[PDB]
Amino acid sequence: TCANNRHQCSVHAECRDYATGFCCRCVANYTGNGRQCVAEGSPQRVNGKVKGRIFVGSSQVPVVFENTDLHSYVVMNHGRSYTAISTIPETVGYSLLPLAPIGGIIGWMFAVEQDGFKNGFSITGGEFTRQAEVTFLGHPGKLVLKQQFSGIDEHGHLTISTELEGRVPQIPYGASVHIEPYTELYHYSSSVITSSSTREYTVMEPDQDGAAPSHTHIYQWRQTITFQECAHDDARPALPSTQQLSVDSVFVLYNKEERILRYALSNSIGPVR
Amino acid sequence: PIMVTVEEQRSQSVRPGADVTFICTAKSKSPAYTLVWTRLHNGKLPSRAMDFNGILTIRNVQPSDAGTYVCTGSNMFAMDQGTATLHVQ
Ligand SMILES: [Zn+2]
């Protein structure tokens, strides 16, 4: 009951008792799932570590990195997520350029909410597990991604731990990548959200005299998002079975000098159109 | 932990229809840091605005675009801010 476990709720939330138990709910002008809440229109930061074991192209020896930092910035209701990942080796930096979804999950979490639809943070409170896989059509193997989000920590930071393992095609040193606007469908069912999407991306050759023509490639993203929802509050409206994420203004960049990988994108969440 | 610098031409004046660009950079004691532009008080950028890697580009400027813009530098340790101003003829 609340009298016993009010501390389980966010300080910016209200507690309510029910037959089988209690549930938390963010107060007016705050968004979240009750256990975690943030003020509307406020800037938020996400921090965590990144470790990987990635085979590039046809290499039989993987590039390994641990203790790499991930820092992301967003402003509630603006819809744009900016992610930086640094201490990323040049040996893998360019080949990770097409993987904007590494930071894209943060865009899903804070997408601009339209009509009667909720973004990732409203649904999970930033407490969830993301299992993702990506297959590059025409190339061997696949890349597996696992990310754990643990809510807002003692410092006020949202949290995210990232693990990457597998094989990705080789992208020429100094090349750049372009991704056009797209939409993704997120299906909900009993505390589980899934999505699968096949998209294309363009690779532009190294910016030097004689740069050859650009070329496109295709990959398929598959992901499963798991989390907990309060099992009480019978009079609780069910979440939509399907929500559409609209993505645009995508930018990806890798800088060899500072060895930093950057991803940026704009997001809106609403009905299927 | 982090220091922001709005590159020269912090104050610009253009006519309606032009494109304007503002640049932001920073010195950080941490490897991973971000640079993000917004209007004053964390106001939402115009739809015609593009913002990435510290570079803010506003295309086909409208009188309503006039005002102060803020570049926010951030890392796991702290944040810092610098400003720029736009005037429309
Ligand atoms: Zn922290």
Image (cartoon, grey):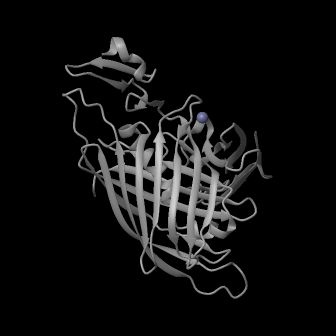
Classify A60 as above or below A166.
below
* Residue A159 screen position, x and y as percent: 53, 40
Q: Is residue A4 left or right of residue A150?
A: left
Question: Residue at the spot x=47%, y=50% of the render?
Answer: A147
Question: Residue at the spot x=62%, y=53% of the render?
Answer: A84
Name the image quarter holding the C terminus of chain A. bottom left
Q: Is residue A250 left or right of residue B88?
A: left
Classify A143 as above or below A28.
below
* Residue B4 screen position, x and y as percent: 75, 44
Residue that sits furthest to the front in the current view: A60
Tally of numbered tags: 0
Is residue B18 at all visible to an observer of this figure?
no
Splitting the image into 4 quarters, where does residue B73 fall? Answer: top right
Name the image quarter holding the N terminus of chain A. top left
* Residue A117 screen position, x and y as percent: 31, 43
* Residue A233 screen position, x and y as percent: 23, 26
Residue that sits furthest to the right in the current view: B8
Ligand 1: quadrant of the figure: top right
Q: Is residue A105 left or right of residue B56?
A: left
Residue in the foreground of this view, choosing between B63 and A228: A228
Is residue A63 at all visible to an observer of this figure?
yes
Splitting the image into 4 quarters, where does residue A88 fall? Answer: bottom right
Residue that sits furthest to the top in the current view: A3
Residue in the foreground of this view, choosing between A169 and A119: A169
Residue in the foreground of this view, choosing between B88 and A185: A185
